[PDB]
Amino acid sequence: AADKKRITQKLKQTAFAGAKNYQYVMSEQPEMRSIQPVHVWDNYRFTRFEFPANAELPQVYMISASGKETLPNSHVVGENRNIIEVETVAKEWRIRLGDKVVGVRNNNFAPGRGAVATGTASPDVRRVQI
Amino acid sequence: AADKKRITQKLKQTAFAGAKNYQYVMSEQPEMRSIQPVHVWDNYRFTRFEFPANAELPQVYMISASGKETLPNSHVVGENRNIIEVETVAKEWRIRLGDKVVGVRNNNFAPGRGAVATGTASPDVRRVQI
Amino acid sequence: AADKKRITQKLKQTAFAGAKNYQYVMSEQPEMRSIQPVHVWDNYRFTRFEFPANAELPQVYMISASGKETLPNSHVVGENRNIIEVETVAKEWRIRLGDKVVGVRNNNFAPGRGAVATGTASPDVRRVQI
Amino acid sequence: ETSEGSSALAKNLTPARLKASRAGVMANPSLTVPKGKMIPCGTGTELDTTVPGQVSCRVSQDVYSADGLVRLIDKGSWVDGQITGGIKDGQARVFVLWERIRNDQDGTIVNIDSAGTNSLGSAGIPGQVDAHMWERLRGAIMISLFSDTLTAQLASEALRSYMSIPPTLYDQQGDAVSIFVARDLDFSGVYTLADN
Amino acid sequence: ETSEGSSALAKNLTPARLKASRAGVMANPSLTVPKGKMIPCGTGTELDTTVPGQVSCRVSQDVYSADGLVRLIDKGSWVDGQITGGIKDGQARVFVLWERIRNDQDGTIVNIDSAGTNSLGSAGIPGQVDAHMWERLRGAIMISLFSDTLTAQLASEALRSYMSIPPTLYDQQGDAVSIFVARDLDFSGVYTLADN
Amino acid sequence: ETSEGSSALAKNLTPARLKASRAGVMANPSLTVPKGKMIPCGTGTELDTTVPGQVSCRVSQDVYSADGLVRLIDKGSWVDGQITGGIKDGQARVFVLWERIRNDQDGTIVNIDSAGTNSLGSAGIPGQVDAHMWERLRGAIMISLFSDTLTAQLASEALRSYMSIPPTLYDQQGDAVSIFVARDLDFSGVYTLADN
Amino acid sequence: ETSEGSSALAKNLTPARLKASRAGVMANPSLTVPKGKMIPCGTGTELDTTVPGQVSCRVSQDVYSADGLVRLIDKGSWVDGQITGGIKDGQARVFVLWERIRNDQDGTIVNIDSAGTNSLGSAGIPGQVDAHMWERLRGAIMISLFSDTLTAQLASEALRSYMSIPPTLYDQQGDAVSIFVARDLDFSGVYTLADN
Amino acid sequence: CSSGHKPPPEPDWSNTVPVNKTIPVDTQ
Amino acid sequence: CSSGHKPPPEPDWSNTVPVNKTIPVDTQ
Amino acid sequence: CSSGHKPPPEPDWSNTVPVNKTIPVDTQ
């Protein structure tokens, strides 16, 4: 319904959950450091990189297992809207932007396990074919 | 409403607020000095550079974190109308104009914090989708 | 109204006022000297250069702060009609005319102050949007 | 019947008077999956724009929506395409035309008609160059050894020969790749909400 | 049927009698976001006008209005575009055509049809030159070593060869860039007031 | 069907019998802002007729009226324009087409369709020359070193090459400039009187 | 269908039988300001038929009538014009097209469509020559140094190059000048008498 | 022969400081 | 080979005097 | 190479006499 959807959609906003990985390590360059993030975290590959007002907008990419680089399909989200939610696999992440080039590392491996069936993007909501 | 808007819009003019950064430092050249500003201040990147009648119109740009230059999307505003409100990130600012080239520095860093959700440009007014 | 305008417009003719700068200094060449002005004065950049009957019509320009030259948007006005009212910033002024080339200097600096909001060209009259 | 290049200049002075763009909202993300997307597939054949004809990939990870909050296009969506024919000379890489992206279990075909790109994202999945400078050269090179052996337009004509035959390419199998799906997918006629 | 270049001169004597311009007011800034703007986006793919086909950026900071008092166009507005094909010879930089600027959460697509520019603002996002002088040269250079070895129009024809193949470009990923959105956006059918 | 050049001479003997000009008065200065004006703007982007596409300026000081007694066009009127494409050979300066001059707070757009000029006033805002003599020359210069090395129409053809590619320009950012707005603005439908 | 050049000769024997001229009186001088006049203006911009586009002058002293007894056209009548484009080779001076002469306080526009002239009166306001022989020459001069270095139609073609690019001019700012306003102004619909 | 691509600008691997500052909350 | 861009005219870094004069108010 | 513009004819800086004669009134 109109109101059925609504309630649900809110449910869907909040799903940056599961047991997160708390530690991301980053690089550190005197140029990088400056325009660094606020908080960057993950539970999945669905990773959030929040930004301060006064922190530039990098462009970040993922390092697939190939080791070679790739570009993630990302988006930013938030009331803050600053954060960039990326929806592609990768441990590391580069965070280029012209000369400069950071590269936060994600740091978790529960290997060989993790897969389930979300059943949408975020598990809150669901797909009930039409 | 017609009158509802009005009242609000005035509310919106005045939002060069928050806790400002008071100190801007500039360069200083004997050529610059002359056609310098009156007051230049910021609370955000929303920065105002007031001008006297008899002070030329520079063209100023922003130094993004890339360090390389960029051009800001600016406007001037004011009954005075002299001031130039710029709405792009950057600490420094150049202020070229032919040969001459000033470069006021903004000077604040509350790093890692600042972001919120204005919800318009200026927080006075708001966006209530149509 | 028809008569409302009129009265006002006269009001608008006379606004070569404020506290003038009385001293303009000029150059002085034996060729210049001859076809010099009568009175040249300013309160603003709105500067008047009156001419005698028997004094040629120079062409004058402004020296913007860039130091390089520019051409002013000028006009002449007056019952006398001889005077040239120029409406562009500049301290100095050249006053070329073929070979010859004078260059009256304006001489005031109340720096960092002056700006207000005229609200038209001349402050007599006003703009009350239609 | 004024001037023409009067017009043109005039066009580009006030720049532009390009027609206003309707900044109108895509209703939903689950109404529209915007491009600006990559369809990060995975190629599963050898590729050789040597020979025109088809390559095939299948999706890798998932494709998403506008906001990017719903996961509509999912993996195992096999795509198929075609390389109309050989690259040009030393061209970095072939060009690729992924046509239909079909889905596996579900169905979810869709003639997407987009080009493929690279990991990097640049258009066309890259490869290696068979110059074939040989076959293009062997011509005048036999003949000319004969005119040479007279002692012990053929250059120009040999160039007209040369350009005739294309080179070829090559890109290996199982290459990570992506599609600049240059458009919009609706899955707002599958997928909708909700909890839990 | 007077003189023509009689006309033309006549045209340019009283300069101009160009037709009066209606100096009319854009009603609102929240009626119109004027260009003269930069859409300061951020490119998120590798770029290579090597191969025609698309680049993608997304907005960086915000876009504003006429007065510049309202913030209508906000960040996270992904744009997508296209480089029709390789630059010319040693051309400073490719040219870029950002087509649709779409918004993220909201919707806010809009076929903007503007070119991109540079940080500096100059049109077209710059890059590096693959001259490819090689492939264009290797032709006459093999052949000619043979005419050379006769001892131990081909130049003209070789030039007609040469110009044939374009060079290419390149611009890296995550380049700060902007769009000279050469037009006007209405978001006076989203966004309106008010307090607090 | 008399003589033609009978006519022409005849035309230019009594010089001219050019048609009388209606020396009619522009009613008001606040009815008309005459050109012969400079729109003394201030450019706020880098400029490079290297690449076609847009520059942007915004007004500097104020624009006035006929008599010059009213100040109608005020500052902060952003203008945008376009450089259709590269200058010619060693041309002093690019040409510039400021199209729409828009105003900031108010509105006051206006497709002005004028060229820009210089501080000096001369038409077209000047710049610097990238000759690019290199790329135009590197052609025959590789090839010809080979015909040279035979020892250790290509000149004509090389010239047909050469002229092909334009040079480029450049003008820096924040240049003081002006517009020969080649026309008349009415702000007699904004602005009127009065005291005090 | 007699002879033609029978006619022509016949035409020029009794010389001429040119058609009688109506020696009719211009009613008033305040009905008509005759040309044969100079509009002794004063140029207020730099001028460079380097770049096509506009110059601007404003009147100097006054313009008068037929008898020359009334002073109708007065000073401060700003004129604007245009130099369609560069002079020819070593041409003494550019040509100038003053179009509209507008008046200041009053109004008094008038598309005059006359050329400007010189102090001397000769048509076209003079200037200086940028030959630009350089850019026209640098072509064959690089190339030819190479054909020269083979040792240590290109001339014809180089000439076809050369003439291609125009030179340019220049005339300084604030030049005393005048207009051969090649016509008649009525101010018999302003100005009339009388005493004291 | 030809050249390849230049391997990527490689971030500091040596220095390595943690990303996060305070601890993250959900914004959205 | 080719040339690049010339790095920008760089303002006085040595001398450094404060901008503001009196203290700012809001105009608008 | 090429030439530039010639810097402008520069007025007497040495001799410097005041402009005004009597004191100005408003005409208009």
Image: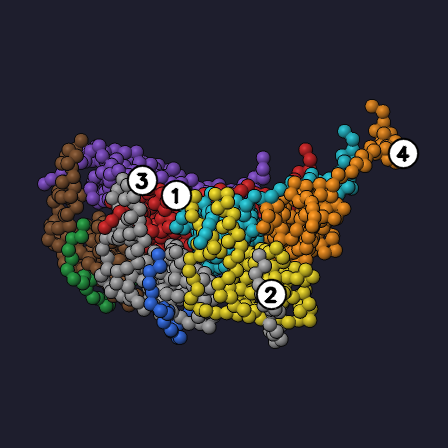
Chain colours: A brown, C yellow, D purple, E red, F cyan, G orange, H green, I blue
The chain letter under disc 2 is C
Q: Are marks 3 and 1 on the same chain?
A: yes
Gap in angstroms between the C-alphas marked 3 and 1? 14 Å
Which disc is residue E27 wearing? 1
Which disc is residue E19 wearing? none
Q: Are marks 2 and 4 on the same chain?
A: no
Disc 1, disc 4: CB below 8 Å? Answer: no
User: Quarter-wise, where is residue D57 in the image?
Assistant: top left
Mark 2: amino acid: His
Gap in angstroms between the C-alphas marked 2 and 4? 65 Å
Q: Which residue is mark 4?
A: G14
Report the mark closest to the observer, 3 or 1.
Answer: 1
Mark 4: amino acid: Thr
Q: Nearer the viewer, residue A17 or C89?
A: C89
Report the mark closest to the observer, 1 or 2.
Answer: 2
The chain letter under disc 3 is E
Q: Which residue is mark 3?
A: E189
Counting residues from the N terminus, which is met first, the one under dot 3 or under dot 1? 1
Above or below: residue C92 compared with residue D185: below
| Residue occupying image coordinates x 40% and y 50% | F104
Disc 4, disc 3: CB below 8 Å? Answer: no
Q: Secondary structure at mark 4?
A: loop
